[PDB]
Picture 1 (cartoon, helix red, strand yellow):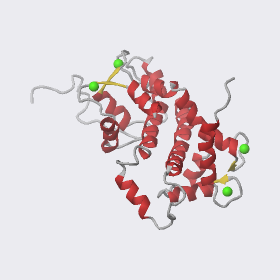
Picture 2 (spheres, protein in one colour; picture 1 turned 180 degrees about the vertical axis):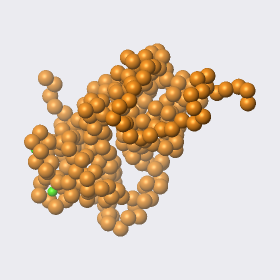
Picture 3 (cartoon, chains in turn purple, blue; picture 1 turned 120 degrees about the vertical axis):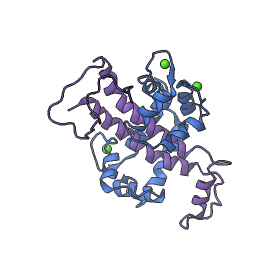
Picture 4 (tube, chains in turn orange, red; picture 1 turned 60 degrees about the vertical axis):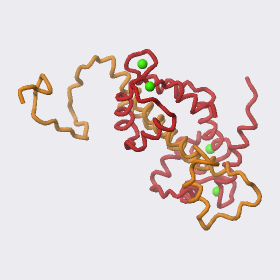
Length: 115
Length: 148
Ligand SMILES: [Ca+2]
Ligand SMILES: [Ca+2]
Ligand SMILES: [Ca+2]
Ligand SMILES: [Ca+2]
């Protein structure tokens, strides 16, 4: 294999460690980019949590057939004679999801701070 | 200046009505766990404590209506003012022209912030009917989040 994948060729394999460590060189890719890197962490968390949040309510009448069957089968619920519609269920699931969305906003603001 | 919205408050009040279950008029951490189980989820007690941290000015260990209203209302400010989610998409744009490459989009969503598997990022692409080519616009995602 005459061709080389990386020009630098510093090492045969690259090791990645989860812990940050006490001392490390910052590195250079264009330092101004690292301002975006701190901001991206809450943005990434909010987008993922928002998508998870929206998917629970995505459909009722035709789609979300499996969810509808699972909800109907459970024993605790009463026959729903009084109200045909079920928004309250949709509101209830998407209400718990936003607590994670809001606390991810606070925690990933803390991740932005590097304290 | 503008009058507060009663129709949106009514959704919040129904959620509050459902959420209280020991029936004392206020929602505590173990009731939130009780709601979670009823949605098929059994999170850790520490998680239930942590996800409540936001809600209260004074930290009263149980959630009163305006604080519950603020928790529910806070999401509405993102819906009403869509600037936060719109800007949250914007910080990932590699070229600055409003179109984001598909290959770039998968790695920064999957491996960063909250971590989600390939099957979960498939739903975001497919259910919004995004095209095979690299240019993906993110304005449509904000509009999908806010139009309905
Ligand atoms: Ca209660
Ligand atoms: Ca309070
Ligand atoms: Ca672009
Ligand atoms: Ca495209």
